[PDB]
Amino acid sequence: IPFHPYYTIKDILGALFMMLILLILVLFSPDLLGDPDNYTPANPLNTPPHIKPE
Amino acid sequence: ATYAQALQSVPETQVSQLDNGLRVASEQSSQPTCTVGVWIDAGSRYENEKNNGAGYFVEHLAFKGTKNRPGSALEKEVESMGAHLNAYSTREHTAYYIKALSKDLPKAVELLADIVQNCSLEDSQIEKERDVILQELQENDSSMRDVVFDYLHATAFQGTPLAQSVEGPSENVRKLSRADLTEYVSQHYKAPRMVLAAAGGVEHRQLLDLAQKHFSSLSGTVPAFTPCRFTGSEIRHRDDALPLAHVAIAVEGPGWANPDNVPLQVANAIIGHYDSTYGGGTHMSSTLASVAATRKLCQSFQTFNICYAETGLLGAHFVCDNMSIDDMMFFLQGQWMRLCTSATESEVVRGKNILRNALVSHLDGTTPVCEDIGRSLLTYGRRIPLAEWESRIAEVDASVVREVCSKYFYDQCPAVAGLGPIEQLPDYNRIRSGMFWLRF
Picture 1 (cartoon, each protein chain N blue to C red):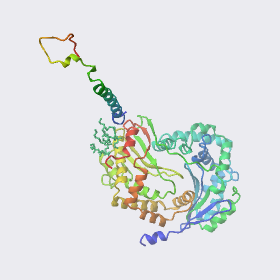
Picture 2: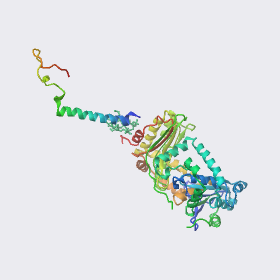
Picture 3: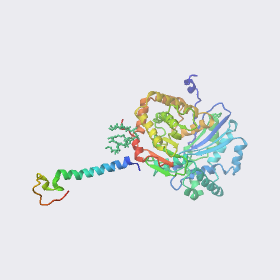
Picture 4: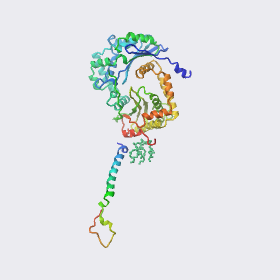
């Protein structure tokens, strides 16, 4: 089937859903996937209790 | 003669009416020949699913034999006096016309009664004609134009009698019996839905006398059809083994009377027609035709205005190779939208002249004139004189075309029937989106 009449609108719907999830994340719980210790100035003389990556 | 006195001088077609309702109509002239025919208001549109194809069967059986003229005797009279007997049955009309010398008009009319009133419908003849109709159906499968037009009617009037083909399904052909044919001729060849139309050197008084002497003993004084529902769809009979791909796209057109017929034809005359073996080609003023000739997109195209009593199909049918359907569909939709959005005076004048030529040149010779008489009396209820056609075309202008095409083409769901290597054919969403312009 041609891409334009069908999959452009399908992709628009997909983008809408992804924007829903991303905007929920940013607006309601921004520091959900992050780590609170990242809100501390970097001090090379002391380490955080845990060292985990993203 | 300034083409005004010419139109005014065309002989008037006298129309009368018998007590049975026979609308006897004739158009006298000076030729020594004549065409006298009977136009029935029968056809596949008046046939249910079971009875479908009975009209074609009856038409086939019409000339074989009659009760008064057993078998070839009916043929014997036709040839021995040089007459050409012929019949044609479309979706909403039937006709039997016998071209013959003006002297033999008394005989021909009598035969025309015998064919219509006292048929034979012999059972062995029915079997033979059943076989013949089956082979004729296999013949009709060959050419793509008729197949595509039947597909268009099926997909545009789905669920309605108009979708039915004229010949009917092959199933009905085998299962149609003599009782069905007798009932069909009894309830569809009734006197009120009859037009005895004659052209050439026949005087109306003589025609009336002959009709009153031979057609008097006909029906006295019901399946009066139902308004069919246009349903924009698409049928794709993808068959890549075929050489060329036939496409036909049509929108719901006007009715038979529906004065908008006069503008639309003019609009269609703007698009015109073209094929490979034409003349000027890349210089023809039809933009679509010029593009087709320049880029060799198609081997043919035409604009049709098939119009029935309450509805009709208005659109274009084109035959092109397997890898030019998209481009020509685009250009066709572009021409349509250009006409709806901006018609321009000069193209309208060209269309008016072209339509004048259509109506005038088509009405020459006894056979087309008689056919026009029958069809007009059946559909319009009168015979629209050529002067009236001239006035109606003269009233058309650029604004009228721009409005009438807009009412029928712009943002309307079309019906598409493609057959052959039609992979290139755009998806129905693209075709529908072609009907409207984001620049307008």
